[PDB]
Amino acid sequence: VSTSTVGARRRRAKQQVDDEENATLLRLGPEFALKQYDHDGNEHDLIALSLSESRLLIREALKARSRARNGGVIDDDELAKVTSGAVANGVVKKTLDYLNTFARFKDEETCTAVDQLLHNSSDCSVLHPFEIAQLSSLGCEDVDEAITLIPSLAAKKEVNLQRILDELNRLEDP
Amino acid sequence: RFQAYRKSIKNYKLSDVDYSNERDWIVEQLKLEKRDFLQHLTQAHSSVAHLEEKFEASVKKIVDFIAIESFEVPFIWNHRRDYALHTYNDDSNNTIIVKLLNEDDLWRIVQLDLDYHSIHDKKAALSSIYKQLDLDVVDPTYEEFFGSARTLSELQDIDDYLTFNYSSQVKNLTAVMKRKYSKYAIYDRIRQDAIYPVVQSIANISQMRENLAQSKRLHQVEDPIESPMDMIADIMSTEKDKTTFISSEKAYQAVKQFFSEQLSYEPFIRKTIRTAFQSFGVINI
Amino acid sequence: MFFLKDLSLILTLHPSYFGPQMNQYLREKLLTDVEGTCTGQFGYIVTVLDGMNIDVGKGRIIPGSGSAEFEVKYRAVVWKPFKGEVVDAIVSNVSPIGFFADVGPLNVFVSTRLIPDNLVYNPSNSPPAYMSNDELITKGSKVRLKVVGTRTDVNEIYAIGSIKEDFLGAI
Amino acid sequence: RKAAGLIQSIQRIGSNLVNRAHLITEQLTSKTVFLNMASFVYIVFDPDVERNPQGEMDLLDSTRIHPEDYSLARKMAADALDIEDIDDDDESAMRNAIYEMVFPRSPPKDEDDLTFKLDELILDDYATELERKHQLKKRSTLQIIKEELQSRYREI
């Protein structure tokens, strides 16, 4: 139904192996490529979202819509009930339940610090945004465990993986 | 049919002690289920003494047939129904037949023997776990609740109690590595911390268990000479090196939650609540 | 995995709605028709950012049918699983053929052939579960699984998980 | 699976089964399976083939009486005939006694068949004797045997 900003893609003869979806190989397909275009056609990077960032964004947008619908005058159940559509209500309920029951960072400032650490780091300047989201989401504790769960980080050995993991564990609220 | 029933059952041939325990458990299960039938039979045929004893004997014989001799239900009903009915004579010496069981009861026998064969492995696993614990003093609660253990829920309660009160020992025995977080790590830290003596001083565990089992006061819970906040703060100040807590209120909350966990993992409270709910509970929607 | 995407929708409006409240009505129609839907190409659209300030542009009158056609561009949060990805889950059902878990709106089915052998299914347990000596996974239990395959339907996505590798199973 | 294998073995051996004992002798089954299924499977007896006493097709094979109780059925038949010459171990005489009782060569002068005379036997005495001799509660079994002799496979 909804159409992406990427169009064309007409017939050719060559066939490529970087077309199939694969998280381990970091092949996310054309619609999830590293380079995207906005409504103005300017350069844009793929925007991944960790569960903390996703929860913050969904809560902010939902509460903004709820405030707007009431003339600009917190509960997840009420917030889900704000939306229209029984199937939409169920889907947003399930997403909210997942995010709440696996929220590593429920505070705006903790998520901001985590994003700053995972973005401004010299080692992380090469890290793929999908890798960053996976690291902030799965909450791994060990370099070996992270490498096993994320095969992409195995080839990136120029990363201070263990100390970054310890920093995330520190930032994680016990 | 028996092969299909026993396909999931890896170990079927029980020992003689296990066999007798299975027979007793099956008899008790039938008595619980057929309580109305047994009561009506006893009330109507009150003249005959120990009709239910003959019922237990017949149930034991039927279980013997099905297990040892591998007899299907219709064969038993067509050629061994003499055991299933007790012919007594009244005051007039008229031969009166008493249908103690029906074919549906034989199907119930098969289902119950399968159920006990299933739970036998679980009870053996709990016994092996307890033996691996190798307690210096045999826990009276363990013995008391294991002797009366009939349902797998009670076995799970035993497992929870043993794991909670021997979390360090159980973790060591597991060690005797996937970094799974032990849910009892906080309680182990409390045990290692200097505030654990305060938790002892709240109430004696053995005295609490004796009082609860007796259902009446055998000992009086002695109140410590200083308030919980007083003792917590004093120990925190005198053991700042070892007290992992930050504030006295945090230690107070940790002590309260540890006491709540201790009370929750007590098998007797769970058993009493379960009996009360099963007896007098209601259903609301 | 969650993402931010710039999506576009074609909205057709009947002439009976050609009133002053046309723009707001288009906004709520877009919200009702996009929020919660499931497209195989993108996955699941969960929310639309800035839902009350979306530009709709000028609608074009379809020749011969009167209805106006609007091109609506918006930014939305989208979740889509990928092959070979390890995510958290909550078990929703236990069955002899396998157990069903839930990863947000997606329901994932894991067959016994993708489960470690020591986690023998126990139907006698209450509730029935796939349990081992040190592991017990039942309804409501947190599980860490790796998505192996995804099946595309008309407006649904079916994923298959596995716990047979390391750092998987119960968590 | 077991029924398919059994019917295949029977078909390979021949057109029909001779008697219940052949289910064991011809290696058609094991022991417990045979004991369970013994009374529930039967072969239709025919007085036309009964002419030879050496007939392997036992008449009791067309009854609900278990093969393990064929001797008891023979003893009851001898009890009804009131013939004390035959002892408890002359199985050929018991077979001839059943032959006479169920299919007499001379039809009875009255309308009461020799199987009817089984009603005069007291089942309680025989049950008590069996329980004393070998500790067996078989009074219901004796009743079933008497019923089967009175009518072969009455519809239930």
Image (cartoon, grey):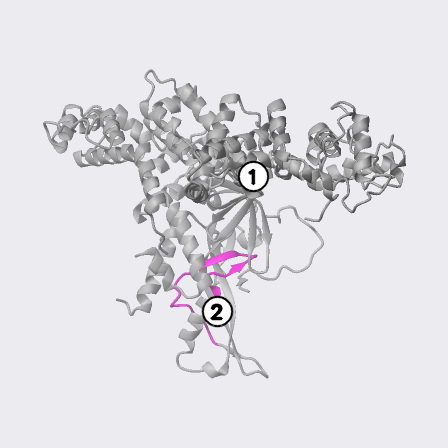
Q: Residue at x 36, y 28 (%)?
A: B145
- For the residue pair D105 and D136, the one nearer the viewer reads as D105
Q: Pick whichever, D116 or C34, lies toward us.
A: D116
> Residue A107 in the image: x percent, y percent?
31, 47
Q: Secondary structure at mark 2?
A: strand
Asked if residue C81 can be seen in this view, the reply is no
Which residue is rendered at x = 42% and y = 47% of the image?
A: A50
> Which percent across, then down, holds residue C116?
55, 34
Q: Residue at x 42, y 32 (%)?
A: B150
Horizontal relation, residue A51 to residue C10: left or right? left
In the image, the segment drawn in magenta is: C33-58
In the image, is residue A56 above or below residue B231? below
**Which quarter of the image is occupied by the C terminus of chain C?**
top left
Q: Amino acid at mark 1?
A: Leu
Q: Nearer the viewer, mark 2 or mark 1?
A: 1
Relative vertical location of residue C101 with respect to residue B48 in this rendering, above or below? below
- Is residue B244 inside the magenta stretch? no
Spot the residue most to the front.
D109
Let me know if residue C38 is in the magenta part: yes
- Contact flag, marks 2 and 1 (Cβ < 8 Å): no
Q: Pinpoint the chain carrying mark 1.
A: B
Q: How many marks?
A: 2
CA neighbours of label 2 inside 10 A, class few (<14), some (14 to 19), many (20+): many
The residue tagged 2 is C72
Report the side of A67 relative to D125 (left or right). left
* Amino acid residing under circle 2: Val
Quarter residue D113 falls in: top right
Q: Which residue is mark 1?
A: B106
Kindly state the secondary structure of the residue where label 1 is placed.
helix
